[PDB]
Image (tube, rainbow, N blue to C red):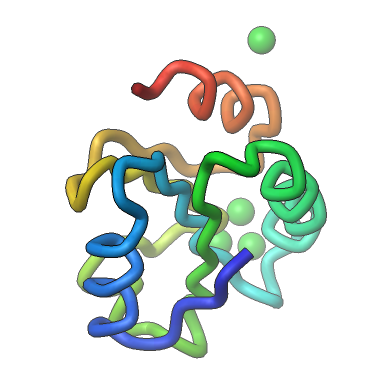
Length: 104
Ligand SMILES: [Cl-]
Ligand SMILES: [Cl-]
Ligand SMILES: [Cl-]
Ligand SMILES: [Cl-]
């Protein structure tokens, strides 16, 4: 999992994923559900080696969370070729797995 820290480093890793799906975990260290799903998000990134996993810590990078309109954590946003295709909020491991498999 790549940690994302600015509006430009976000702009950039999207440009770079090529065709791969990109999943973005918006998390906080003080958020119980974010902490719970953190190592699961990491473990998925060991598995879906053809999917790009990024994390935005909303305290570290509030301007990125603000651009992304993220105020509840954890929120997962999904991007394909530069574009946001879907999102959801909550530490829902089944939904996370299912969505990764759904999105083309
Ligand atoms: Cl919380
Ligand atoms: Cl929260
Ligand atoms: Cl919460
Ligand atoms: Cl279910």
